[PDB]
Amino acid sequence: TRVKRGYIARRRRKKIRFFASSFRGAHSRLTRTIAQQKIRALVSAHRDRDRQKRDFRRLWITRINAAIRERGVYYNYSKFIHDLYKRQLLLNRKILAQIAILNPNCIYMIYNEIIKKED
Amino acid sequence: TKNGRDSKGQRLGVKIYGDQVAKPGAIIIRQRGTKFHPGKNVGIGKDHTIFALIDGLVKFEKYGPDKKKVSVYPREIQPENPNSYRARKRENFRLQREKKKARREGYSF
Amino acid sequence: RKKGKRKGRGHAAGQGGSCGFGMRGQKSRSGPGIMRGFEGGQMPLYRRIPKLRGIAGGMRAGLPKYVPINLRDIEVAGFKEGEEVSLESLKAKGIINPSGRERRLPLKILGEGELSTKLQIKARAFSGSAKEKLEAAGCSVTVLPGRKKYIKESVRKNLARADEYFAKKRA
Amino acid sequence: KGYKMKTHKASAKRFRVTGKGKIVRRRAGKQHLLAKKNTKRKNRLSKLIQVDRSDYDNVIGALPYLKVNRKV
RNA sequence: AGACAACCUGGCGAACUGAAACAUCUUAGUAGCCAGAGGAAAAGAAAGCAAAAGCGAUUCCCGUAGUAGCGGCGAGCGAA
RNA sequence: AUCCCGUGUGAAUCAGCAAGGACCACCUUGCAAGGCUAAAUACUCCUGGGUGACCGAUAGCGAAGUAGUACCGUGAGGGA
RNA sequence: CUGACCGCGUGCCUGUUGAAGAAUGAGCCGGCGACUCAUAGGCAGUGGCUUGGUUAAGGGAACCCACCGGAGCCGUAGCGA
RNA sequence: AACCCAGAGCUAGCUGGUUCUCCCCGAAAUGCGUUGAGGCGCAGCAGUUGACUGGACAUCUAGGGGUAAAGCACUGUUUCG
RNA sequence: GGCCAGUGAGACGAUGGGGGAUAAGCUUCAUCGUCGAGAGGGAAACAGCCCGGAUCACCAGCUAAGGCCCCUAAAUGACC
RNA sequence: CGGUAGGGGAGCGUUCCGUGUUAGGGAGAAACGCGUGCGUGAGCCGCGUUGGACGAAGCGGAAGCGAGAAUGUCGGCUUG
RNA sequence: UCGGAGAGAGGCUCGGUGAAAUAGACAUGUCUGUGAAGAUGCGGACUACCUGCACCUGGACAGAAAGACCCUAUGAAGCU
RNA sequence: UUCGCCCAUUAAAGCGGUACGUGAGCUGGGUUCAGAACGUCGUGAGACAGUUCGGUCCAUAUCCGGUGUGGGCGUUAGAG
Ligand SMILES: [Mg+2]
Ligand SMILES: [Mg+2]
Ligand SMILES: [Mg+2]
Ligand SMILES: [Mg+2]
Ligand SMILES: [Mg+2]
Ligand SMILES: [Mg+2]
Ligand SMILES: [Mg+2]
Ligand SMILES: [Mg+2]
Ligand SMILES: [Mg+2]
Ligand SMILES: [Mg+2]
Ligand SMILES: [Mg+2]
Ligand SMILES: [Mg+2]
Ligand SMILES: [Mg+2]
Ligand SMILES: [Mg+2]
Ligand SMILES: [Mg+2]
Ligand SMILES: [Mg+2]
Ligand SMILES: [Mg+2]
Ligand SMILES: [Mg+2]
Ligand SMILES: [Mg+2]
Ligand SMILES: [Mg+2]
Ligand SMILES: [Mg+2]
Ligand SMILES: [Mg+2]
Ligand SMILES: [Mg+2]
Ligand SMILES: [Mg+2]
Ligand SMILES: [Mg+2]
Ligand SMILES: [Mg+2]
Ligand SMILES: [Mg+2]
Ligand SMILES: [Mg+2]
Ligand SMILES: [Mg+2]
Ligand SMILES: [Mg+2]
Ligand SMILES: [Mg+2]
Ligand SMILES: [Mg+2]
Ligand SMILES: [Mg+2]
Ligand SMILES: [Mg+2]
Ligand SMILES: [Mg+2]
Ligand SMILES: [Mg+2]
Ligand SMILES: [Mg+2]
Ligand SMILES: [Mg+2]
Ligand SMILES: [Mg+2]
Ligand SMILES: [Mg+2]
Ligand SMILES: [Mg+2]
Ligand SMILES: [Mg+2]
Ligand SMILES: [Mg+2]
Ligand SMILES: [Mg+2]
Ligand SMILES: [Mg+2]
Ligand SMILES: [Mg+2]
Ligand SMILES: [Mg+2]
Ligand SMILES: [Mg+2]
Ligand SMILES: [Mg+2]
Ligand SMILES: [Mg+2]
Ligand SMILES: [Mg+2]
Ligand SMILES: [Mg+2]
Ligand SMILES: [Mg+2]
Ligand SMILES: [Mg+2]
Ligand SMILES: [Mg+2]
Ligand SMILES: [Mg+2]
Ligand SMILES: [Mg+2]
Ligand SMILES: [Mg+2]
Ligand SMILES: [Mg+2]
Ligand SMILES: [Mg+2]
Ligand SMILES: [Mg+2]
Ligand SMILES: [Mg+2]
Ligand SMILES: [Mg+2]
Ligand SMILES: [Mg+2]
Ligand SMILES: [Mg+2]
Ligand SMILES: [Mg+2]
Ligand SMILES: [Mg+2]
Ligand SMILES: [Mg+2]
Ligand SMILES: [Mg+2]
Ligand SMILES: [Mg+2]
Ligand SMILES: [Mg+2]
Ligand SMILES: [Mg+2]
Ligand SMILES: [Mg+2]
Ligand SMILES: [Mg+2]
Ligand SMILES: [Mg+2]
Ligand SMILES: [Mg+2]
Ligand SMILES: [Mg+2]
Ligand SMILES: [Mg+2]
Ligand SMILES: [Mg+2]
Ligand SMILES: [Mg+2]
Ligand SMILES: [Mg+2]
Ligand SMILES: [Mg+2]
Ligand SMILES: [Mg+2]
Ligand SMILES: [Mg+2]
Ligand SMILES: [Mg+2]
Ligand SMILES: [Mg+2]
Ligand SMILES: [Mg+2]
Ligand SMILES: [Mg+2]
Ligand SMILES: [Mg+2]
Ligand SMILES: [Mg+2]
Ligand SMILES: [Mg+2]
Ligand SMILES: [Mg+2]
Ligand SMILES: [Mg+2]
Ligand SMILES: [Mg+2]
Ligand SMILES: [Mg+2]
Ligand SMILES: [Mg+2]
Ligand SMILES: [Mg+2]
Ligand SMILES: [Mg+2]
Ligand SMILES: [Mg+2]
Ligand SMILES: [Mg+2]
Ligand SMILES: [Mg+2]
Ligand SMILES: [Mg+2]
Ligand SMILES: [Mg+2]
Ligand SMILES: [Mg+2]
Ligand SMILES: [Mg+2]
Ligand SMILES: [Mg+2]
Ligand SMILES: [Mg+2]
Ligand SMILES: [Mg+2]
Ligand SMILES: [Mg+2]
Ligand SMILES: [Mg+2]
Ligand SMILES: [Mg+2]
Ligand SMILES: [Mg+2]
Ligand SMILES: [Mg+2]
Ligand SMILES: [Mg+2]
Ligand SMILES: [Mg+2]
Ligand SMILES: [Mg+2]
Ligand SMILES: [Mg+2]
Ligand SMILES: [Mg+2]
Ligand SMILES: [Mg+2]
Ligand SMILES: [Mg+2]
Ligand SMILES: [Mg+2]
Ligand SMILES: [Mg+2]
Ligand SMILES: [Mg+2]
Ligand SMILES: [Mg+2]
Ligand SMILES: [Mg+2]
Ligand SMILES: [Mg+2]
Ligand SMILES: [Mg+2]
Ligand SMILES: [Mg+2]
Ligand SMILES: [Mg+2]
Ligand SMILES: [Mg+2]
Ligand SMILES: [Mg+2]
Ligand SMILES: [Mg+2]
Ligand SMILES: [Mg+2]
Ligand SMILES: [Mg+2]
Ligand SMILES: [Mg+2]
Ligand SMILES: [Mg+2]
Ligand SMILES: [Mg+2]
Ligand SMILES: [Mg+2]
Ligand SMILES: [Mg+2]
Ligand SMILES: [Mg+2]
Ligand SMILES: [Mg+2]
Ligand SMILES: [Mg+2]
Ligand SMILES: [Mg+2]
Ligand SMILES: [Mg+2]
Ligand SMILES: [Mg+2]
């Protein structure tokens, strides 16, 4: 019983093409290229969902270091953090970064508690 | 002149060591000349292969003053450890095989 | 019904690409292989070993000449006393199914197991232990004649001259 | 009329089977040059040996009608 | 008298190939070519099988059997 | 062995002759060197019926239209 | 849907000790395009019978198929040339 | 050593290719033989299936040995006295 | 034991050596690690070096090797 | 619970057959196009200001059964 | 030496007609370093508005398929 | 031919790298291709890190790189 491949192929191709919408140039056109480009996209995605978790801690820490450095002459990120722990506070770095921007006065207070107690 | 011929290593040398176990007939040493001498309960071959005549522990000795001789002595194994680490774990394996095979066909539902 | 491997479709499936033939060279190449009994050109095992005893020269192979039966089988079978055993009645109860070569054969009895009954047995031959156990159990042993070997007259004269010698000597 | 496997004949003049189903063979080398082989060796080369597990494949493959138990 | 797909009979009759080379062997009396006749052809009415018991022209199928055998006793071939 | 042929020699007639796997004896079986014969079996250029887990215009015949055509080749031939 | 700017990111296949390779292959797109069938041997998984199992050709209200068809074949003794 | 057709789908231990998805386990590039060396047979090391088993990782003791070091008792070699 | 595979061109690194010139990213063995068939981090980039062996999600947290002037995460830290 | 060669398990789809002259379908089937739908994925389920007559699901069966590589191959269309 | 001028046919512009080899996709700098040991594509610096046209040929291991040379094949053929 | 030798000068007539720096810029030899001849080796077909005469390399610049020469746009209203 002869079987033409029929649409079984074209569907697959089409469902790939949908993926690759808005790729500049022949990456959005030719099937054969589109394949690869799909794979690479998916791959980067996977990679950078891991990079992401690295990079926001990067960021947050940076912003925090900026936010503290303003108060004391001699004060750091490092110093700060060590002080947060020996005072037993749980706040992670996302929260201290977002509170650094969006509620600056709060961070000033926190610093004043760590200082009072280290005193 | 031009070298490069040689021989497969003949497999000579001590086959069973001191205080290991030997069967009767079991070869203790293959040697070229006699680097050892036959002791008691122990025969020697044509190539000076030394072999055991009796089951037991093989012991090397000073032939005196210089050379060495090997002889075989009958041992005694009574001391089976009733309760010890060895016995405990081997038993455990037995009983686990038994249990784990018996709770199969003994499974409801 | 277990579904078959279709090789050469996809990798994620199964044996794709190479199909499980690994890389290249003779075993992965299409076509008849190399002979089953052949090792690389080293003298093959079967060729470096000498031919079996009689076969080697054309001495005819040894062949079964009777259908062997023990007493075990005659016990297990439903034989009531007086019953004739023979060949035929063993096909009847089926404990022997003869094929072509076996059809053309006679019957022989081999002692094993201990028979309890009185049977009337017919066969062309018996082992020693056989007819010993049989005549011990009170069974009648009928030994059937084999087909005469044709002999030309001169050899009858010789073999008879013998018998006349023995007869004149004992008498 | 299909095709049925052929017994490899040069393999069947060499190997055979024992009643319990293991393959056996002769030993090589007792043919000529016996004078210089000691009697003890000659006796050893006279007997029937069960074929090495290793070759069982090749053999079995070339003697398809040999009834053989590999002890399973 | 010529024409006529395949089948068939007769005549000539390869080689690549397999044998991990090759020469005996294999391929295969296959392809091809020539000639011939038919709807089938050919074979066929025991100077035959068999084995001390029997059969009763030829052809074809199943089986015996990948058995007996043949064979650089190799590759392989293979009955009744 | 049996069977059939080149060269050369070359018998016996039933009180014979041949075969029975070198050969000889014995027995068994058969009657060569004249012919002819149906069926069971092989095949599809085809004809008539039937069916199709066969194709559906890149498939199915090379050919669903000028198809062995157009075209190519001195020619055998290739060939949409 | 677009994308200011930051970060990360050395086409695919084949094949290799090893490739982004300046190693091979693909202009692009759509079709066609490859472990198939028959017959045996071995092994496994499932059934069926185990009053041992099974039929081959053949016959069948055309096929299939009921019902036949035990000739064969496998298992019941080995040792030995 | 012409062409065309056929044997012919010759043969190619060579090169190229061999198409759906998920899950589990997971090598080797070594030895021997080979008209063999880029091939193949067997072993070694995969997977899956059974039958036996009781170990492994540690700790300590016991064996035989002739390397590193060391030495001049032998075999060479060597300087001066 | 059964059934049934690949593999039989290896690379460097540590160490023991031979060949070579105690030359070679050379060559050939021996006992190991990694790559092969291993992604992540450190090594500017960088198969074989160091850390560590990736079921998967998280805009959570602690560390290894390695680092804390700016590019670029952390001390323009302390004391000799 | 990394993974190549490679082995084993569990699945999805394509055309056809059985159920079957089936359910459904000019009140719009196949197909073609779409989705804030559901799947570990192969894919499924839903929707159409296209299309114009066929044809599921379930439980089974069979293969000319899944393509991106063959300096593959045939058409179409580019680049220069 | 040591080039010069001129004439024709092109080259160049305009109108008409209009190919080809090539080609994974190309958003296609230089230096230096790295790397299968000669990189637009990886690193660090440096230089670079966008895009035509005419010219030039250093690169893209430029293009036109088996490498004639070397080796392999138990390949092929010719010759002795 | 790398090397080198000489003639006449000269301030001096440097040595190296750039794939012989440079063959899609040019041209000789060299890969001694097929013809032929000599010496030599080989019975021979033929051979030679011997000699000798003859003996086909193509190219419309895609991109980078370059020498020139424009347009667009920017230069915060538009221009000379
Ligand atoms: Mg169809
Ligand atoms: Mg197809
Ligand atoms: Mg986007
Ligand atoms: Mg030695
Ligand atoms: Mg003695
Ligand atoms: Mg199949
Ligand atoms: Mg599978
Ligand atoms: Mg692939
Ligand atoms: Mg396989
Ligand atoms: Mg391949
Ligand atoms: Mg292989
Ligand atoms: Mg082949
Ligand atoms: Mg064969
Ligand atoms: Mg012999
Ligand atoms: Mg026998
Ligand atoms: Mg039988
Ligand atoms: Mg038997
Ligand atoms: Mg003899
Ligand atoms: Mg095997
Ligand atoms: Mg006529
Ligand atoms: Mg005629
Ligand atoms: Mg006619
Ligand atoms: Mg031949
Ligand atoms: Mg030939
Ligand atoms: Mg063939
Ligand atoms: Mg051959
Ligand atoms: Mg061959
Ligand atoms: Mg007829
Ligand atoms: Mg006739
Ligand atoms: Mg008659
Ligand atoms: Mg007559
Ligand atoms: Mg005759
Ligand atoms: Mg006869
Ligand atoms: Mg005669
Ligand atoms: Mg003749
Ligand atoms: Mg006469
Ligand atoms: Mg007769
Ligand atoms: Mg007559
Ligand atoms: Mg005659
Ligand atoms: Mg007649
Ligand atoms: Mg006639
Ligand atoms: Mg058409
Ligand atoms: Mg057509
Ligand atoms: Mg159509
Ligand atoms: Mg960016
Ligand atoms: Mg990067
Ligand atoms: Mg970048
Ligand atoms: Mg290479
Ligand atoms: Mg490339
Ligand atoms: Mg490569
Ligand atoms: Mg290479
Ligand atoms: Mg192609
Ligand atoms: Mg290309
Ligand atoms: Mg296919
Ligand atoms: Mg196959
Ligand atoms: Mg099959
Ligand atoms: Mg089968
Ligand atoms: Mg069963
Ligand atoms: Mg029938
Ligand atoms: Mg019929
Ligand atoms: Mg019928
Ligand atoms: Mg001529
Ligand atoms: Mg020719
Ligand atoms: Mg042929
Ligand atoms: Mg072929
Ligand atoms: Mg061909
Ligand atoms: Mg050939
Ligand atoms: Mg694992
Ligand atoms: Mg290794
Ligand atoms: Mg080879
Ligand atoms: Mg192997
Ligand atoms: Mg294993
Ligand atoms: Mg010691
Ligand atoms: Mg010690
Ligand atoms: Mg010593
Ligand atoms: Mg030593
Ligand atoms: Mg020393
Ligand atoms: Mg000394
Ligand atoms: Mg001394
Ligand atoms: Mg080897
Ligand atoms: Mg090697
Ligand atoms: Mg290989
Ligand atoms: Mg190394
Ligand atoms: Mg080393
Ligand atoms: Mg040493
Ligand atoms: Mg030195
Ligand atoms: Mg060294
Ligand atoms: Mg090396
Ligand atoms: Mg370490
Ligand atoms: Mg590999
Ligand atoms: Mg690893
Ligand atoms: Mg890594
Ligand atoms: Mg890194
Ligand atoms: Mg590690
Ligand atoms: Mg882990
Ligand atoms: Mg921390
Ligand atoms: Mg910083
Ligand atoms: Mg400081
Ligand atoms: Mg893991
Ligand atoms: Mg896994
Ligand atoms: Mg795999
Ligand atoms: Mg469906
Ligand atoms: Mg359908
Ligand atoms: Mg209806
Ligand atoms: Mg619809
Ligand atoms: Mg349909
Ligand atoms: Mg659907
Ligand atoms: Mg469905
Ligand atoms: Mg209508
Ligand atoms: Mg249905
Ligand atoms: Mg459908
Ligand atoms: Mg097909
Ligand atoms: Mg294509
Ligand atoms: Mg091309
Ligand atoms: Mg084309
Ligand atoms: Mg001029
Ligand atoms: Mg002019
Ligand atoms: Mg003109
Ligand atoms: Mg113009
Ligand atoms: Mg074109
Ligand atoms: Mg650009
Ligand atoms: Mg380097
Ligand atoms: Mg570079
Ligand atoms: Mg760069
Ligand atoms: Mg980049
Ligand atoms: Mg250029
Ligand atoms: Mg030019
Ligand atoms: Mg490139
Ligand atoms: Mg060879
Ligand atoms: Mg040859
Ligand atoms: Mg001067
Ligand atoms: Mg001066
Ligand atoms: Mg220069
Ligand atoms: Mg120059
Ligand atoms: Mg150039
Ligand atoms: Mg010249
Ligand atoms: Mg001469
Ligand atoms: Mg010379
Ligand atoms: Mg001339
Ligand atoms: Mg241009
Ligand atoms: Mg330019
Ligand atoms: Mg400009
Ligand atoms: Mg301008
Ligand atoms: Mg302006
Ligand atoms: Mg302006």
Image (spheres, coloured by chain):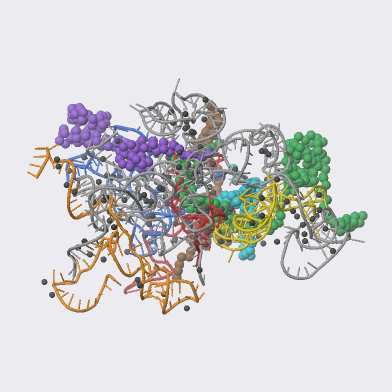
Chain colours: A purple, B brown, C green, D cyan, E yellow, H red, I blue, L orange
Whether residue B71 is visible, yes or no, is no
State which quarter of the image contains the C terminus of chain C.
Answer: bottom right
Closer to the camera in the image, D65 or A71: D65
x, y percentage for residue C16? 46, 44
Residue B13 vertical placement versus C99 (above, below):
below
Residue nearest the observer in this picture, A27 or D27: A27
* Total numbered labels placed on residues in the image: 0
Is C43 drawn above or below residue C93 in the view shown? Answer: below
Residue at x 19% of width, y 29% of height: A104
Instruction: Return the residue nearer the eye: C57 or C108.
Output: C57
**Visible residue check, residue B28:** yes
Q: Quadrant of residue A49?
A: top left
> In the drawing, does residue D32 fall left or right of residue A35?
right
Relative horizontal placement of residue I43, taking residue A4 as reference (left or right): left
Work out whether residue I60 or residue I5 is closer to the camera in this orientation and state it: I5
Instruction: Provide residue E71's location: percent of width, then percent of height.
Output: 64, 59
Q: What's the residue at 47%, 51% (across, down)?
A: C24
Q: Position of residue E63 (x, y in %)?
A: 69, 45
Locate residue C125, reporting x and y percent. Answer: 79, 46
Horizontal side, residue L39 vs residue E45: left or right: left
Identify which residue is drawn at 51% across, 50% down.
C30
Query: Is B80 situated above or below B56?
Result: above
